[PDB]
Length: 50
Length: 311
Length: 114
Image (cartoon, rainbow over all chains, first blue to last red; front, side, top):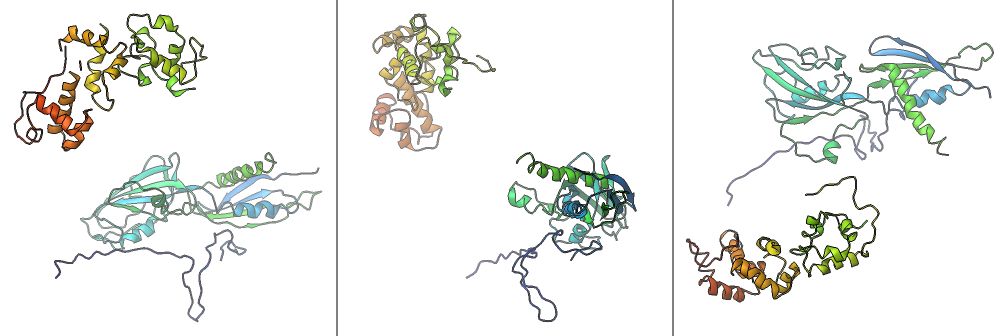
């Protein structure tokens, strides 16, 4: 019944969004909620923030 | 009042990538008032240059592979991100690269311009492994701020792009890590005053005084706003362009009348007595004068603009 | 002298302005006086019909639209009123005229370039 198959391939890129599951190696699940800028992250005495 | 203002002291550069800069003397409670307020501004909206697009031969898309390379193609994207260029007079430039032979291309290899100051010579781009290879890449450089990686540029603007251009994810911010510490400045009667030691660790492409001087241009713009803040269309056309019948209006422009304001300021009795008017053209003159609301010989104030041309 | 201006406006307006003699009376003068003012100039104006039949005849052969637009584009009354004018002038059916691969000057009235 078929004449021929045409089957194309598409690739994508995907980054951290709200609602993207996130966990360590101990069962500590997490919904990533909010993406904060670098200033309003808490920062140590020597500059490099959390 | 017993006010006081702080001033420039010094700039001590460790290198192009590290420096320190003081500021003194502030009064009580002022050191964190201006101190953190710059740390939130020198990271947020400090403008600088970055890499916007790359176009490159022999490859049609970033997820292919190129012959004669060690690292992959989007690793060249993830190495051309951390380049640092200081453009003096252009918010858009280009640079070309032509390279052959086995050997790692560094930033010295690219063909420069007279006004893009290069910061790092050896920020490693690629690795060549076969001698017959050749490279043509054209690195677009813009100057902006923030982390808009032109993914909104493709999403706010839908121009017809040519096939072959690769879009770079860019961070325009030159400032990386900035912190401060507040020690007591010594004025003999005012022991309460303090200093504002301000550090800075960035890449190149920045003079630090311009960073601090641009901050007060930002703040005092908002700090001003809390102190200071608390004619008929068919009358203005040619007589030929009034859109009338066969011969009623173009007969009027051989009287040199090429504006409708000049029409209403002629005597009707002697305009219809020239040997070119016809006696059924009378009603079209009576049309556009009565439909608009004008009288015979009534003086219009200024019928021409500063543009005055005939045919 | 004066009604020169009627000649090539009529080359341009056999179109959307339906111009009759009373609409041609908008050229300054009366219904009856424009006739003899056009007569001793030309010999032959209501020429207009020829232009309407000539001016419709640009649509048969040189544009691809069918026949029903043509009898109402260039200011004729109806599709029989067109072909009544067509058969009195060109002695053909326009379905026997355009479909024919040959075409020559038998009935098409020339425009007046006096």
